[PDB]
Length: 104
Image (cartoon, rainbow, N blue to C red; front, top):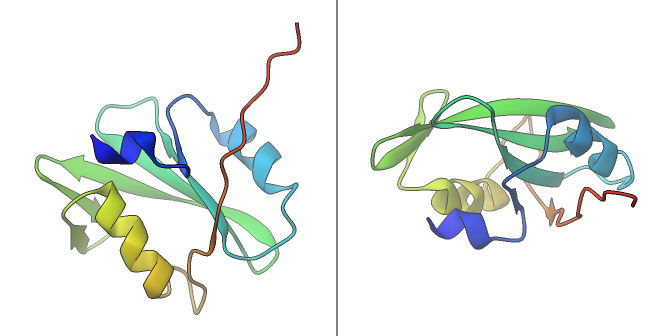
């Protein structure tokens, strides 16, 4: 779907790999979305209050759900949370597009 080509979306990034990337950006609002190793499940990994936090988003047919908040798609969800606070008063602000690198 459309989210898969967005700069904040990572198809193959674990929890720890995501933290490893986010720890290098010293700014609240830094974020990425990663597919989880369970069907129809994604995580938003983000920086808030100086920490890294993870929240889960479920794909539910034609829609996605974050807690009790429904959106048309992952792209619409992220757009909404760039405009409205996701966590306390903090909005998503800095999409992280880093590659998890394999040293060879």
